[PDB]
Amino acid sequence: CPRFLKVKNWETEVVLTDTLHLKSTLETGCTEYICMGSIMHPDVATKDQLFPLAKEFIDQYYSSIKRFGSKAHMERLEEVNKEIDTTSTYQLKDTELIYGAKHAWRNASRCVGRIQWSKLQVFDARDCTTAHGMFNYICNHVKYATNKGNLRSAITIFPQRTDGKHDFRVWNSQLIRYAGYKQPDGSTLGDPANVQFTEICIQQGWKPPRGRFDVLPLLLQANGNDPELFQIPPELVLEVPIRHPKFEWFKDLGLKWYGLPAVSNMLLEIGGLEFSACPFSGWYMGTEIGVRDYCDNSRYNILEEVAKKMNLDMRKTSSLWKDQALVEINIAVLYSFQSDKVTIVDHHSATESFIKHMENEYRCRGGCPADWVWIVPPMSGSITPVFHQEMLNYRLTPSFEYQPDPWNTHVWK
Amino acid sequence: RFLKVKNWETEVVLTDTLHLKSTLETGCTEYICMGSIMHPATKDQLFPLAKEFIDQYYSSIKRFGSKAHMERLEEVNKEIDTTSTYQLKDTELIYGAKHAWRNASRCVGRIQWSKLQVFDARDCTTAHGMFNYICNHVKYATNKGNLRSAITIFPQRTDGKHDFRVWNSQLIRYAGYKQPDGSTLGDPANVQFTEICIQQGWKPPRGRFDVLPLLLQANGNDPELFQIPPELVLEVPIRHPKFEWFKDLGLKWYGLPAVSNMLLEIGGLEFSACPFSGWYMGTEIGVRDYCDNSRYNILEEVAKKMNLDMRKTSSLWKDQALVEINIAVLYSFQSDKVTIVDHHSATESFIKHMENEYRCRGGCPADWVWIVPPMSGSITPVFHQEMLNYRLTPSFEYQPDPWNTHVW
Ligand code: HEM
Ligand code: HEM
Ligand SMILES: Nc1ccc2ccc(CNCCCc3cccnc3)cc2n1
Ligand SMILES: Nc1ccc2ccc(CNCCCc3cccnc3)cc2n1
Ligand SMILES: C[C@H](O)[C@H](O)[C@H]1CNc2nc(N)[nH]c(=O)c2N1
Ligand SMILES: C[C@H](O)[C@H](O)[C@H]1CNc2nc(N)[nH]c(=O)c2N1
Ligand SMILES: [Zn+2]
């Protein structure tokens, strides 16, 4: 591979040089003859696989704190190697755990909010042993991160995988999501994205309210045991009713959303160690709710209803009634969050901040992996600066990874 | 291996086998994706490429290995020997041009690929000749507003010293003027090309929408200026169906999008001048041409007239103004009976096209970064459609601007 790769911004003519790609550790899915950049997703580590992965990470950590090649660096390598030899695994120091988590975020090529990467509150939950304990840790996370609307990015990290038959898993895809209910007539009540998980909850004993916005219970698996159900205290669940600054009728749609996006189904990989339960949270970009959650056909799908209330001409697509309604919904979402003083960022501000972040990273780090397909917002793409920005996508470690849904792999006891 | 692409909204899964046919590179590697990078002969190289192309041509007319196929390979080989190149049959030229379009991974309009009027201009020898062929193209493709896809193909490259080039990036474009006060009048994208025309003798009206002259290079000679007869140049005054002040913006655009700076590659042969044209998708004008910061950049003026609150980005004043502008463009073209497609209809057609190609061809190379429209991305079906991108030949390729390689 060439030592220097250039990316250009076609709007500003700014040209940046990437050297960080040389540190790429994993496959992208692409080859020299095919690109899989729009593909959504294109038994443990052995002692011998683990050694060089741990060293890679430890070296990186000591290089970051400007103690590379120091006595403490050499001692740490030695202690880690000993631990791998005698136990087939090792334990991260608190400092290394914090470094790894922050860097997994820094390295997340699909994330547009990475300007914030170094301000991440890391909660060490590696002493956790039961689902009740996981529930305690999760509640504390939600309350801290919510902060009465002044949201603070946080991650809570549960014990790493051992043999793979003792995984900690949060079965929820996010800590706070709304139930979806398939009706016998084929219609869906609530959020169609969550139908399968909802059915699992109901089977595990959850009594569903059967509303449009029912917060789902936590389904928590500790140490490989069968998962258990917990209700999040509703006072911990901050919600924002959606209204529009102009259209008084908008509130009559009865929409609302939760303040805290808290993804809970990803795997955090640090130095060859795998943390299969590591829920993390930031705050929303408005389009995630206003475009995707509300306007996706397979989601709440409200464009038509909004369009009808707006008295739009809905017979020709070329009236752009869909686009017109989509903007007003996104205006309402931002307006409702800002009014209730709940942190939210519009797509214009987020993408402008991301460009600045990316430029800083190119300067201080030699690059910034970025997945254009994901970074460009789902509405008004070219009127944001990221649309015009060439990006290079590659996989650095530590990293957040996808993992199979736990109900597909779980051995029921 | 067979590769599956999924639509995450419809759950439809397609299976790609066609990618196994590609031999050209994408720019990506196993470790680095360059999907968002804009741009990532000899007799000895020539014959396998020719053979490859003749083979797929005869395979496409269901006569692979026929007497005709065999004589053709023989003839081509003989010709590459004695002449260092070869000439395509008419049937082959047309097949090659339609397939270059069919294989254009960045084009959302490909459902139309087999409907392409091919104009053979390979007998052309002078810039006046090129001008004649180009006028005929424009008149044919414009068709009084009922636009028809067309391509005009000028002689292929020989030694690199005698290239035919259309210096314009499109046959019809607006001039851009660098003003004393440092602002730009007209289209900033064309400031440089405009300066070259001016230096070559063009007398500029110095307006906001001055149609550029053609600058035509034949057989490696210095380019020559030509004015396209104005009655051939179809234009649309942009107005809004609700905002009666919109017409007062003084906006217009031309109805015919006719890209003239690409290189058509067929069977090893390179056609450095192959202007082609279809019709507009509305966002090309309403989002990119009008609203890019580096183009006409009108959002602020429009938002003003809509009396929007422009102090905070989170009022989405930009998005509101953007939608209204695109409504105006579609409305204006439709009212003037000039062919245009909105991005909803275009992307729907593209999904149907993909479905067709997978069924009959085993796949469809597609560049998501380019296929998804520059506004309202996820409310169009292609946003949710996984796509595989790979390079098939015949193809359209980028080439250097002639003013960076030309000796006068
Ligand atoms: C603090 C404010 C944050 C903002 C505004 C933000 C924004 C976003 C957005 C808009 C996406 C695309 C989401 C989608 O369309 O589904 C995303 C993806 C992602 N974010 Fe961030 N994020 C933030 C914080 C975080 C934090 C704290 C982490 C981890 C520590 C993180 C890690 C990720 C990862 C791994 C993805 C890829 C998700 C996937 O592939 O499904 N983000 N982010
Ligand atoms: C008939 C109606 C057509 C429509 C609606 C259409 C639509 C589009 C659009 C919207 C783009 C993206 C261009 C941009 O954003 O700058 C594109 C790209 C492209 N089109 Fe089509 N197109 C049409 C016809 C054609 C024809 C007739 C040809 C060739 C014979 C063609 C070949 C291409 C190629 C090669 C690209 C990629 C250009 C590049 O890489 O810069 N298209 N098309
Ligand atoms: N505001 C934020 C911050 C961080 C986020 C991290 C992740 C996500 C959502 N990822 C959604 C994946 C959706 C999906 C669907 C089907 C298959 N794979 C993935 C949002 C964030 N938002
Ligand atoms: N409606 C149509 C039909 C066919 C088209 C073919 C091409 C294009 C535009 N190509 C734009 C490339 C712009 C660019 C700028 C800088 C570097 N590389 C490329 C539009 C079409 N529209
Ligand atoms: C097919 C395509 O890869 C898929 O729809 C992607 C496109 N880009 C995205 N970008 C973001 N931020 N989030 C998404 O869910 C997606 N979905
Ligand atoms: C950097 C990025 O590749 C560039 O801005 C691309 C993005 N997608 C595009 N898509 C289309 N249709 N046309 C374009 O000019 C671009 N520009
Ligand atoms: Zn790629």
Image (cartoon, coloured by chain):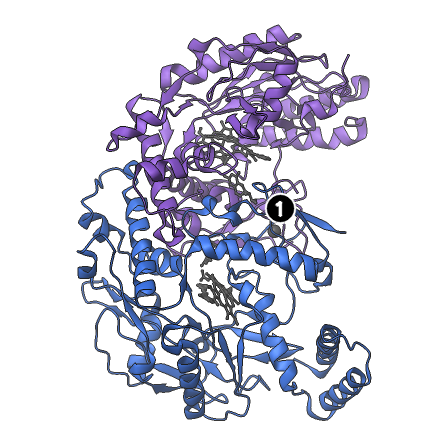
Chain colours: A purple, B blue
Q: Amino acid at mark 1?
A: Leu
Q: Position of residue B349 (x, y in %)?
A: 52, 57
**For this rendering, which residue is in front, A411 or B168?**
A411
- Say left or right for B82 vs A14: right
Q: How many marks?
A: 1
**For this rendering, which residue is in front, A263 or A245?**
A245
- Say left or right for A160 vs A352: right
Q: Quadrant of residue B271?
A: bottom right
A365 shown above or below B192: above
Q: Quadrant of residue B93?
A: bottom right
Q: Secondary structure at mark 1?
A: helix
Q: Quadrant of residue A399?
A: top right
Which residue is the site of mark 1?
A: A22
The answer to whether residue A274 shows anywhere in this view is: yes
Image point (63%, 77%), residue name? B95
Estimate how packed mark 1 is, as few (under 14), some (14 to 19) or many (20 or more) residues with alpha carbons within 10 Å: some
Image point (49%, 88%), residue name? B220
Q: Position of residue B371 (x, y in %)?
A: 51, 55
The answer to whether residue B364 shows anywhere in this view is: no
B279 shown above or below A362: below
- Say left or right for A408 vs B242: right
A268 shown above or below B351: above
B386 shown above or below B116: above
Q: Position of residue B130 (x, y in %)?
A: 45, 88
Q: Chain of mark 1?
A: A
User: Which image quarter is the C terminus of chain A in?
Assistant: top right
